[PDB]
Image (spheres, coloured by chain):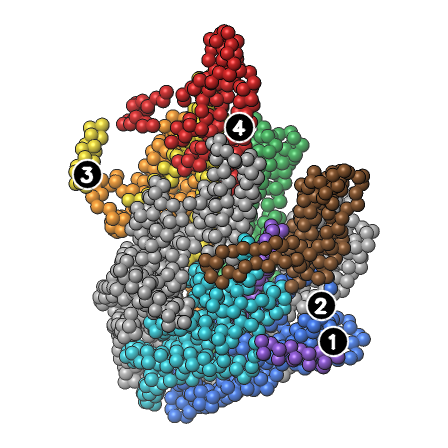
Chain colours: B cyan, C brown, D red, F orange, G green, I blue, K yellow, L purple
Amino acid sequence: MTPESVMMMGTEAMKVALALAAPLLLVALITGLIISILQAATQINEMTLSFIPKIVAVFIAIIVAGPWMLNLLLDYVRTLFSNLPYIIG
Amino acid sequence: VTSEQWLYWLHLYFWPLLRVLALISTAPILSERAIPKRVKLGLGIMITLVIAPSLPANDTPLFSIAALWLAMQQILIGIALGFTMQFAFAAVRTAGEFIGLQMGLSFATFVDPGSHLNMPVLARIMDMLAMLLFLTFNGHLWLISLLVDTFHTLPIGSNPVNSNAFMALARAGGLIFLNGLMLALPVITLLLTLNLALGLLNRMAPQLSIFVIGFPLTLTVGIMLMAALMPLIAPFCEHLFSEIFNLLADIVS
Amino acid sequence: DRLDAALRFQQEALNLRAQRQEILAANIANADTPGYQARDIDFASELKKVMVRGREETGGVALTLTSSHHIPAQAVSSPAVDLLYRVPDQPSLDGNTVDMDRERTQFADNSLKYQMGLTVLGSQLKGMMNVLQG
Amino acid sequence: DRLDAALRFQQEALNLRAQRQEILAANIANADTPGYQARDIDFASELKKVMVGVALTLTSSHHIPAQAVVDLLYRVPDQPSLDGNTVDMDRERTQFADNSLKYQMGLTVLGSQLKGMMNVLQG
Amino acid sequence: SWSLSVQTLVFITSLTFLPAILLMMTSFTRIIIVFGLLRNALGTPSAPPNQVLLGLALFLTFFIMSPVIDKIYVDAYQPFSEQKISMQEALDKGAQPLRAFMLRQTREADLALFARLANSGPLQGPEAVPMRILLPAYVTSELKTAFQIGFTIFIPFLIIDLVIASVLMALGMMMVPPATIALPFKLMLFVLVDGWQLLMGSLAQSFYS
Amino acid sequence: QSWSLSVQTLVFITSLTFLPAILLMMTSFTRIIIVFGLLRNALGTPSAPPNQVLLGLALFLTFFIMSPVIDKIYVDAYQPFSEQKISMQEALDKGAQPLRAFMLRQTREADLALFARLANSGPLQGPEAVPMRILLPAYVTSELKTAFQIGFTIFIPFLIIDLVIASVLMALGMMMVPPATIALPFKLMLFVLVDGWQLLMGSLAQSF
Amino acid sequence: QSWSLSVQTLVFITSLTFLPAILLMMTSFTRIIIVFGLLRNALGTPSAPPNQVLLGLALFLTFFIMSPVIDKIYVDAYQPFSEQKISMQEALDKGAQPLRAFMLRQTREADLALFARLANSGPLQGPEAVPMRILLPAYVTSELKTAFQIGFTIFIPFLIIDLVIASVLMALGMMMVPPATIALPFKLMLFVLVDGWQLLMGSLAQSF
Amino acid sequence: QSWSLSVQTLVFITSLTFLPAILLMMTSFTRIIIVFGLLRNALGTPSAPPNQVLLGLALFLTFFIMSPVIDKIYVDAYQPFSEQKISMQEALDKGAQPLRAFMLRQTREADLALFARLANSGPLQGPEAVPMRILLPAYVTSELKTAFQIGFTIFIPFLIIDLVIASVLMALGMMMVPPATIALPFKLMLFVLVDGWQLLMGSLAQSFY
Amino acid sequence: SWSLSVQTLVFITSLTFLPAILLMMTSFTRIIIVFGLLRNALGTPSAPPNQVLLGLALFLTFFIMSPVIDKIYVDAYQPFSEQKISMQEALDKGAQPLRAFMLRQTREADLALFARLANSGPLQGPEAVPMRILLPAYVTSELKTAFQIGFTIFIPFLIIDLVIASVLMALGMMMVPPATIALPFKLMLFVLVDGWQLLMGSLAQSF
Amino acid sequence: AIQGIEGVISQLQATAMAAVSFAGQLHAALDRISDRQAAARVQAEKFTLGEPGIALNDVMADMQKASVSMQMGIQVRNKLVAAYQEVMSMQV
Amino acid sequence: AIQGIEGVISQLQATAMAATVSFAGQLHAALDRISDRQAAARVQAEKFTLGEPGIALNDVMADMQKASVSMQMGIQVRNKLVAAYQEVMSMQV
Amino acid sequence: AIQGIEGVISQLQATAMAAGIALNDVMADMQKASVSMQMGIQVRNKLVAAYQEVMSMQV
């Protein structure tokens, strides 16, 4: 009820969002950086060949860590809906 | 006996109802479409039932241009109060949308302005957070109390009016921008530095950077930055509400 | 103001019809009382008079009731109409001029004219709800 | 039912008036019977008695429900007849006319009450 | 007591205000506001059709207001029907359990504000609060509680859209709408975590707590 | 014991007011209409088939699905009531049985358990002890959940097409094009080459 | 057997109530309306022709297409009824046949089989005896499928134009130039030059 | 032969409902608003003047365009109606002729031929004998085609500006600069200096002649 | 003076056209278009909500109509009570200040075009322009004025965007999009100079 | 209640320091109409009882007046309900 | 029934242990009250037409009018309830 | 009032510059009040509809 509780609500929610999005974004960033440094080493420059492995890497990311995200988000929503009638004002 | 003078009761219960309902239809949270219309009408009716008997009853007939002037006055007062209150949420929405646009979340606006493709999701997040904070600080009760109080300052009866006062509400349009800049400032600046950092990377081997490495990094950095910046809005939320409230108190009179 | 002024003529005519019928009923009630001159009012002149200057009463004063336990009481009250005497038709030994044919003809005529006033006023009020309704 | 309590008094008065009407007409019809005593009822006392029962209990469907199933005062004679008949024409004719009038009045009152209860509901 | 005609007239007239009692004196407002907000959240403004949500809200309100209705019936309707309590006293007797139910769920701040707006004297205990103060205080408290519940409801459905947009933006697909992708995932979430049982139980507890 | 004919007429003509409510809450109309709206959202165009056509088609589908229940009601309640062999109340009680069975067969256990918890129900026992006022909201909740389960998996192929087209377009280089604009004709092609309408009706019917 | 006059006018007014449903689910209005909406979406102009203009055009096209069926109904059914030659029941039965034939001409056998199998209808010998309750949903489904086919096919030339302009812009290095702004005037020019409106209406009429 | 007063009132009030349909399918309005719907797209601002401003401006322009037709209808048909020298049926027959001529002069022959063939009409001796059922949809079709022609022609100078600005931006190596935002103010410049609105309305009015 | 019921009918009917009066007769279109163009200038099409812009334009319109409202009050509101003039002579007398304002804000070319569109040859004087010719001409003049003000607003933001892009290109960066960098600088320039208050002051001065 | 009497003395102290409604009017009108009807009914029952002094003229006139008062109450209720329905129909 | 007697003994056990309003039940009770009032008046008219002694015409008419008043009560309550339900169900969430 | 007499003299300066209850009454005032209330409701509805049409704009 108190504004401290509200702002905590937003923080924990958006940290959950950060945890959900961090693996995919970080995998894409690492793949892009690796392809870019390889291009710099080989002196190859086409703006389209960096887009190819990124999709494959990010799609594999759901294969490997997808169940973890799905279990984390469901637990968050379940706990939020269960604690809903105790943060009422 | 068995009089029950109806015109007296109607004139006593009408104009306060007009002002209360005019505030209701525009005041934030009390004007959200999710409330059924009958609930809003009943709240206005009950508030008027509580308030009106204490006020001096007016005797101007409903079939006169004076009644039209009175109705216009009540509508103006109600919409002015509600809109001045709404300005703070407008400012919060502006700050959130700008943080989100510096995230690169909606890049299609820079190339196709107003092209039916825009999602200010951060703006919505902080808008609903601001609504929750406003609910916590009981701002709506204050709004109702000030709606009641503006009578003593400005009675139902037609009273003369001023000018630059309207400018004040219009000049409040500056606040939406001015306060929005500060909220952002605590994050956009660092994001700016990040973009500057990306520039240093592009000053190296040409191409092979930006649109491939900049976007995910800046998205994650914006996310964690403003996630850490979330505790900061609440003092600024109270500052915004106080600014709107004392501006209203000073200018309505 | 405008609506009050537009409906004021027929309303006042209907009130005067009611008072005239009260007077005629009083004449009919006292039809066998010895020494009672029949009373009646000139409807048109009194209607114009009430039109120009608002309705007034002889007395109609009453005890004031500031508290909630004061006993309410009102003294005699009557309209400000001029009660004129009807010309008798034929003499009578008891000494009343209430001729029953005249009384019952005026009663029926006043009845129909009051119903006419009700019809006109109701038509006007519907003629207005028709506009307002939407 | 509350509706019965409102209309109980007038219904009982109407029924008592009908019964006393029958008794008075029986007195008129038997005027010539030698040895016949003129009988009547005291309307007020009997109305008190009627205004001032246990349906047997039905356990199932086959069980049969309970099956349902005034005091006459002699008139004081006025003239002594030789055949023992105490019926007086004038007294009972006046009583008969009065009872007819009161029966009509009771019908009027009961109809007015029912019509009021109706116009309350109509709409 | 009143005549039977007057009692019938009053009963028929009072039968008119049933929607007003349902909306301004009952648990209906919070449930309907929460349902509207949730429908706004999932991105399907016409999904459970208004009639389906209205029927569900009516059944929920009937299940929630059961003890109050029972107390009214045992204390007011039963003596009135048995000609033990007059018609003008059954209303006063039955307005008390509803008043108590409205009080418990109301808030001090609203009560203080509407005690000040009426220029009434000090209210040392809750037993001195009339209905003219409790009615709008209860209404405002219910509105605020419903909006709080809906606004904490809204957060996950916007979180999903945020992460969807960020993931789409990582790969450079800047011209893909995020709402169209997020809607099936929001439906999947609301299916997985017992979307309705948890919400139903949370609302019911929110009343009985 | 039987009601008077005036009472029967009053009750019969009053009950017709709940016909839309019965059709929506108690029958298969809700699930079909929700699935159709979700499919319209998934097609990429929000109002291609007018609401009127979808509503009529959903009504016909609901009638065809519920025809066995209607036949059972007619055999059990309508026919023996119209021949003046049973009373109105007993006819309604007898006719509530096949509809109760239909509602139970599609009811989630958790929904029924929760709504029995909220109604203070204690020793329930046989599946034939659930009252109508408890069974109905549980059926509505189960129908909403099932409709959402169907919709979110109806969404899948169109998301696949959208993602494939966007990925191909951006990887090829044309990143300034709107992928949805090019994708909509392909969504229509997929829907017409699979026989999406016929297969969707088959799936909706076989969901019961 | 002939209905009394009051029953006849009750039936007439109740049937007049169902007019939009008959127009949408028994005539060619739905297919034309769907194709018009898809075409409007295809030009990149979501609100250029107002809805009322397109609705009026679809209504007039439907009237012209259904003129032979209306003439058959008038000559065979309505005219004898208006001259008191036949009753209302047999007039309606005779008027059903031409409309039924028209709807059967434009339905797909697979959808008819689906709705027959779903409704548990017994084997039906030939098209002569197919209930209207079976034919109407099948005809609606076939109309939906045909409308989607026509719209998807229509979507092709504008897709060609968009792709060619996007490629021309991209091969010049113009990386941040959106192709919609350049494509919309050329879409309008293409539709104007081929006499698009009259050609598309003629194609819709010829398909019926 | 004249209709009764009740039937005349019924027909008049019933025909009053078709006012938007008559305005769209029989007057100039369809060509105007559609062009506006495209012009706001050419300027790069879909917001543009508000929708109601454009609609009312189109309404005023339509009234000015149909002033001669309205005057001819008022003189030939409605004046004898008010002065009792004609019936309602004859007035309806006579007043439509100037409007039919106005519709025919802007009707392309191909569309008219298409709708004849589609109605299986017999050999029409001359324009004067063309049925309204054939003239109405053909007029609407020709109206749509003409509006699209005008809109595409309007789309030209703004395309010129966009192409020039994009070429200038790319020739300087400023490849990452979106030219739409830069070229929008110059489109506003072009519409202001040339007096775009007045010129466009004059062109539309002259086009109808 | 005609019937009271007809007066009520006419009054409630004329109440419907209130958005038409606000848009076509007052200046509301000008402020709303200026706000839309300014929002398009900063690069954020949803930063202030449409509701807030509409309300700000409404308040600005109320102030800038306050002199005309006062003239209406003097010529129509007051004498309608003293009954020196009423009904006809007054409604038109009260509308006269609107005519003066719209003549002031209307260009001559639009009026000339709309006159030759109505074959009104003998329109010689400038205070007897009919409403049918005055209204659409006034609306077109307002559109032109709003577009000019929008371009004037556009100039500094376009300059800032161009400067940012030029410095990015000169510094060696060829891939960094200049919009992301230039957006916060656009905002800090807009706030620091206090763009909003001067904009409203100029709009009030713009009449 | 003991606390209720405490509250009464508190309100008396409030009055010391300091030194009807539409629903009330409607309740008063209903009570007046019901009292008139009950008086007419009681007089009618007394006349039917046979008690001396009660005249049929007065009974019939009082029943007439009671009927008129009931009809007045019915009309007031009808209008009042119509006005309430009109107010609740207002769109906010 | 055997199961019916099982249910009887179960309800007896319930009474032993013991030693809930219903709107549908209340409506059923009210409809029963109206229907038995009408049936009682009808049967009284039946017996009075058949000529059975003990039945009075005024009682017949009074009972018929009482039944009419009861049915009007029911009709008005039906109207109010249906109007309230329709207005509640015509609302949008 | 003293201020009331001030207002009277002000209006004089302005002139210088310029140079029991029956059913009949109960029902009539009852109807007049109903009419005035309906008029107020309709006028407010028109004003609210105009305001919502203005605010539902698109800028």
**Residue K12 visible:** yes
Q: Kindly identify which residue carries mark 2.
A: I87
| Quadrant assignment, res I13 | bottom right
Camera-side residue of B83 and A68? B83
Q: Kindly identify which residue carries mark 1.
A: I129
Marks 1, 2 in one chain: yes
Mark 1 → mark 4, Cα distance in angstroms: 87 Å
**Helix, strand or loop under label 4:** helix
Question: In the drawing, does residue B223 fall left or right of residue G146?
Answer: left
Which label sits in the foreground, 1 or 4? Answer: 4
For residue B107, above or below residue D82:
below
Residue F91 disc label: none
Which label sits in the foreground, 1 or 2? Answer: 2
**Helix, strand or loop under label 1:** loop
Q: Kindly identify which residue carries mark 4.
A: D102
Of callouts 1 and 2, the N-terminal one: 2
- Identify which amino acid the numbered label 1 is placed on: Val
**Helix, strand or loop under label 3:** helix
For residue D86, above or below residue D57:
above
Marks 4, 3 in one chain: no
**Residue D107 visible:** no
Mark 2 → mark 4, Cα distance in angstroms: 67 Å
Q: Kindly identify which residue carries mark 3.
A: K14
For residue F115, above or below residue G37:
above
Q: Is the Cβ of the residue at disc 1 closer than 8 Å to that at disc 4? A: no
- Identify which amino acid the numbered label 2 is placed on: Met
| Residue at image location 72% in from the left, 51% down from the top | C83
How packed mark 2 is, by other alpha carbons closer than 10 Å (few <14, some 14-19, many 20 or more), is: some
Q: Is the Cβ of the residue at disc 2 closer than 8 Å to that at disc 4? A: no
